[PDB]
Length: 199
Length: 211
Image 1 (cartoon, rainbow over the protein chains, first blue to last red):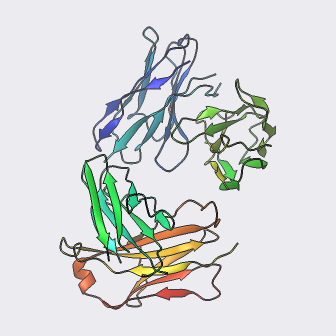
Image 2: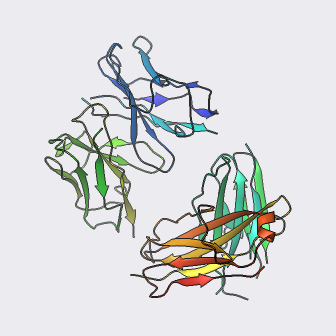
């Protein structure tokens, strides 16, 4: 079997999107389809369901009059027309096959993000120093220390979305006083690569 | 809905060991609880369905049990692959099918945190903002929080913390509490402290800096 999604991307509060979970490996009609989502960081939250031909549909609360699922039992895909999209919805979307309420088969997910700028890297002077990767969108980031040389004593902290929508993380290293230190920051998502010496 | 509560919040075992997970409910859900393994960067997968059953392809190390509210997933001989995030889901009161908030089977004592503080740059202070940063280095257990202080004035909700996953060796954690001020409000003040409270410290600890 092969449940695989598409549709994800960046969208802002207000707009809408449409996904689709195309099917192979099976007779897509004899099963009820599903939509589950993983809000970055959190766990599992089911979003909605649809049946064999498509007349029965129960949605998770938090939606409807917003979310509308459907399916095309002829060309094998499953749909989800999102509207009214909000921040809360920022998440990775999965479509599982129903067994029942037994998602016996999942898909690899598609990412929907609700909110593009590079980070402003500033220095944080045994001892301890580091870099402050601030105000950037979207994620992720990667911070190396001395081009892959300084590894022992590094703690790149998971980041924190802020009131603006611009993430900002911290990476720190503990070094024995007394050598040059540089953090390698790279925001592949915007083409922002930045090195900043530390003193 | 029906609340599914998992615990431990995280399992820290090295291969070979036996890991026991628990999924408790608010009502009876019968033997309708399913388990889900979600390896990193991948997608949820069906482990034990209904509470004892193993869906196609699943090895025997995975054993499920329970009936009613309390359940238990049991991985007897931990394998490097079995290190993922395990979810439990009830399919009794459908809809909404509710999920457990997870349990992470992670790989490989009370230590007070080592505190540091970091004054703002200058290259930052021109845009108009100042970010003071506090660092709580390698400490166990996790639970521990920071109270920033601008001239002995308890500060409220203008900070933001982050925590590393549990180190595999120390068995510790780290934390980045960042206080964010305007450059103006920053220049408007004096002592920038960070009071750390933690189980491995008979006495609360502080780290300050006049600017």
